[PDB]
Amino acid sequence: GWASETAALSETATPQIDRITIPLHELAAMPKASQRLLDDSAFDIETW
Amino acid sequence: ALNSAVAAEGGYLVDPQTSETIRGVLRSTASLRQIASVVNVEATSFDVLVDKTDMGSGWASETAALSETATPQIDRITIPLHELAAMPKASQRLLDDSAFDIETWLANRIADKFARAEAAAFISGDGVDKPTGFLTKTKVANGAWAWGSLGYVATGAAGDFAAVNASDAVVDLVYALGAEYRANASFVMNSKTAGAVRKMKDADGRFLWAEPARLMGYPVLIAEDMPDIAANAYAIAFGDFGNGYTIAERPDLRVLRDPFSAKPHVLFYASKRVGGDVSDFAAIKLLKFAA
Amino acid sequence: ALNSAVAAEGGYLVDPQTSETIRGVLRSTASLRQIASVVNVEATSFDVLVDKTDMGS
Image (cartoon, rainbow over all chains, first blue to last red; front, side, top):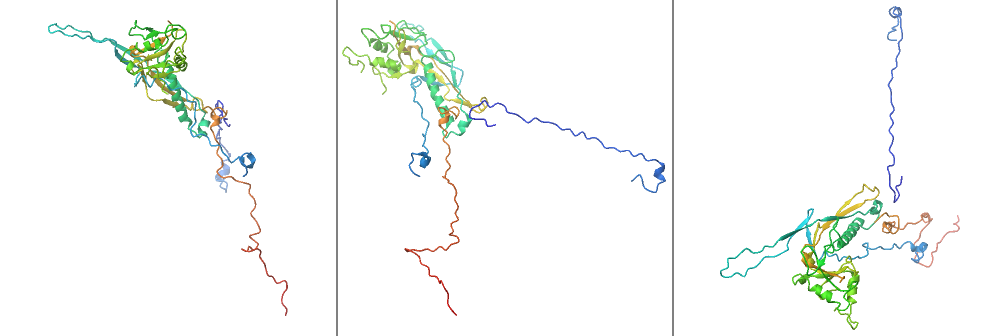
């Protein structure tokens, strides 16, 4: 603030630091493919 | 564009020209420093060494077996060299926007106050944290004069000078001082004592005493810190302060500006340190008004 | 030597600056001279000779 010609000029204020956390979770998927329908199938399911 | 008197019709184009230097009341400077013994000393104290006595001469015979003669005993006097400090507070917004030189004026106005505050200590100051003036030196009647004391001559009447033979207490004070100290000696009075001296007039109304304002031919230092003519006061002193009084000082003024204590101000802290008391007690006589 | 706020203190010796040149409100300079015909005439008056009509054929 404007100090003015005469004043004590006390301590004003300081930005209060706040911390935001990005917990970094994981994204998972487990397609359960049978073994039969994996080698007797003409389509490559393991790459599909 | 018209007359410079009325404001709107061209009166705003004037700008009063201010002073060159910021003047001030010209206060007393007769400080006894210019007549006493000022010695630069960068220490905690000054220790003078005097010879309170003298030797003995023989006038030896042709066959006399010369004996040992006297030898002057020696006195040491310690000038404590106290300090004098003043701390004026000037705003920082002022110092910036103040076309004069406020710092140089503050140091020049302080050095005027110090040269004036130490003039009181050299005359009537006591011993605590300040030089002892020659008035606090156990004044003893003259004739019964010892070394550790200042002599004085009495006037007669208590309130003022003698009732009948006035102006004899002044002349015998002169000739009670020693022909070698009177060579360069001077009275010390205040403004209202030197006035009461000039008002002294003979039996016909004419002044009996005939810019430096000397008295009986000897100079007069018009102090402002000696006592005036009271019931039992020492209003007039006279002596060779060139040898009687010694001043010890550091010939500078240490100013420490402090922008930190008072934050929007600067708070100049200046302090020179000076001390001094009488070193030759035989060289200062006094005029007590008691009896 | 105190603050420059009250008069009988540092407040007397401040002396504001004064805007080295005196300015004024700005007025338009378009004067019809940059379209009209300006003729330097050192006389009591100027005449012009025109042809209010034309010839015949």
